[PDB]
Image (tube, rainbow over all chains, first blue to last red; front, side, top):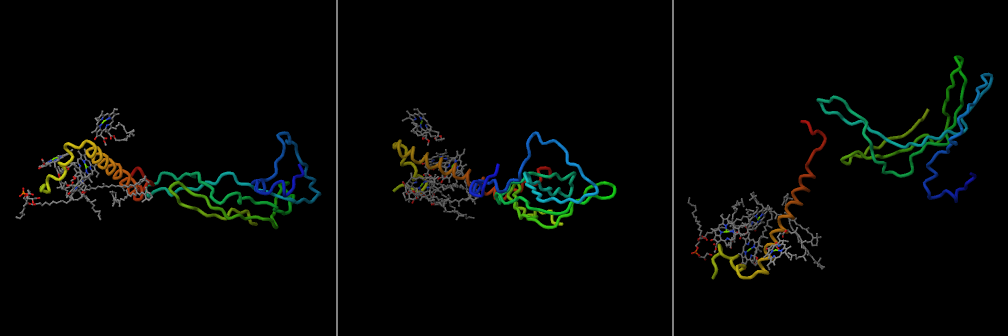
Amino acid sequence: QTLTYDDIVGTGLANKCPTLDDTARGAYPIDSSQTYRIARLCLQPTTFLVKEEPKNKRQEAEFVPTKLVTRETTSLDQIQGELKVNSDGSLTFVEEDGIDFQPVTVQMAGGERIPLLFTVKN
Amino acid sequence: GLPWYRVHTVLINDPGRLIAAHLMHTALVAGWAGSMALYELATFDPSDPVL
Ligand code: CLA
Ligand code: CLA
Ligand code: CLA
Ligand code: CLA
Ligand SMILES: CCCCCCCCCCCCCCCC(=O)OC[C@H](COP(=O)(O)OC[C@@H](O)CO)OC(=O)CCCCCCCCCCCCCCC
Ligand SMILES: CC1=C(/C=C/C(C)=C/C=C/C(C)=C/C=C/C=C(C)/C=C/C=C(C)/C=C/C2=C(C)CCCC2(C)C)C(C)(C)CCC1
Ligand SMILES: CC1=C(/C=C/C(C)=C/C=C/C(C)=C/C=C/C=C(C)/C=C/C=C(C)/C=C/C2=C(C)CCCC2(C)C)C(C)(C)CCC1
């Protein structure tokens, strides 16, 4: 509902994006004569996977799971940009601004730490 | 006096100190297992169980 800062603070919910009901399976029409924008875009990671370094023999490297160690600090949100209607009818979003990066450290088996700039900049 | 090669004969009729020496031997052997494992873990490379 209309929760408040003091409802939320310290709970870990500030790092969660909003959600829609099991029942919001409708459809939003695009009036091609019209102009649009993403007024808020929010991305919340739930898993980080790192590709492993296959040995000189190799055969194939897989993406292995990793442990997040930097806490509920990972989400991208308040992102804005304009949703254009192209001429073949496709929709293209063009980011302008937003909190569009989070530094993040996850940890691979054996103890190797892997920082990354989780971002959608531009 | 006892020769050096006979010092531990003092336990032959002292069942408690015999148990105390046997406990210390056991303690040292379990100790060794622990330390060997930690040294091995500090040096083991698990990235390639093939080659
Ligand atoms: C399981 C091992 C063990 C046990 C339970 C005993 C038990 C006993 N010994 Mg025996 N002893 C041992 C090993 C052992 N000894 C070894 C290896 C030696 C040769 C040094 C002796 C020499 C010895 C003598 C000469 C005498 C005893 C005596 C005794 C009794 C009284 C305790 C005493 O005076 O200790 C003395 C023993 C020690 C203090 C052992 C010191 C050895 C150290 C801990 C080795 C450490 C090496 C060093 C730290 C290296 C580290 C690694 C390196 C890379 C730096 C008791 C029944 C006494 C006794 O009753 O006589 C009747 C006695 O006079 N023992
Ligand atoms: C379970 C094994 C065991 C046990 C409990 C004993 C116990 C005993 N032995 Mg026997 N013995 C054994 C195995 C064993 N022995 C084996 C395998 C051999 C052949 C090598 C002998 C040969 C032997 C002889 C020839 C004599 C004894 C004697 C004795 C008595 C006095 C020993 C003493 O004070 O040492 C004191 C020893 C020291 C102070 C220092 C010795 C340092 C050695 C040379 C190097 C140490 C190696 C290091 C600590 C690592 C341990 C070895 C490894 C196996 C783990 C005691 C009742 C003596 C006896 O009969 O007296 C009545 C005696 O004369 N034993
Ligand atoms: C009540 C029956 C009973 C049981 C269960 C045991 C059990 C044992 N005796 Mg035997 N013993 C008995 C009666 C018993 N004894 C009688 C009536 C006598 C004549 C008085 C002896 C005399 C005797 C001697 C002289 C020696 C043993 C030893 C041992 C141990 C050898 C293996 C070892 O240390 O494992 C490794 C140990 C562990 C994995 C730890 C187990 C810890 C257990 C759970 C005990 C925990 C605390 C407990 C209250 C201590 C008393 C237990 C019990 C031994 C009385 C083992 C625990 C030897 C010993 O003590 O070795 C050091 C030894 O030298 N026994
Ligand atoms: C089945 C396994 C087993 C058996 C039967 C024994 C038996 C024995 N050990 Mg124990 N030990 C074991 C495993 C075992 N150990 C393990 C796995 C470790 C961990 C590494 C130890 C660590 C250990 C220590 C630290 C000590 C013993 C000691 C003893 C002896 C105590 C009785 C005594 O006075 O002997 C009388 C001594 C003899 C009869 C000498 C026997 C010689 C053996 C065969 C070794 C041969 C010479 C040796 C290889 C030379 C080493 C040179 C090196 C320094 C470069 C006895 C012979 C104690 C000892 O020797 O006290 C003096 C002692 O201090 N042991
Ligand atoms: C945990 C690790 C700690 C390890 C503990 C260290 C080991 C402990 C000490 C062991 C050293 C033993 C030395 C005792 C040696 C020593 O004390 O000898 C003399 C000694 C005489 O003993 P008796 O019965 O006369 O008793 C007199 C007492 O005072 C002895 O306590 O004989 C014995 O020990 C019998 C074994 C003879 C051993 C013979 C060795 C002679 C070799 C000489 C020739 C060399 C080669 C040259 C020719 C090419
Ligand atoms: C006290 C205590 C504790 C702790 C403990 C510890 C810390 C221990 C340690 C222990 C250990 C840490 C031990 C180890 C051991 C070792 C050993 C005992 C070794 C032996 C060796 C030898 C015997 C060798 C020999 C040789 C040589 C040298 C050369 C080559 C050849 C041969 C092999 C012969 C606790 C807290 C728990 C509880 C309470 C009490
Ligand atoms: C009650 C009490 C107490 C007690 C104490 C104690 C009980 C202690 C113990 C102690 C101990 C009991 C000690 C130990 C030590 C030992 C040592 C010092 C050893 C060493 C070893 C080594 C040297 C090894 C090596 C190795 C091996 C063996 C194998 C692998 C590799 C290596 C090389 C690592 C106190 C005082 C606190 C006070 C309070 C009260």
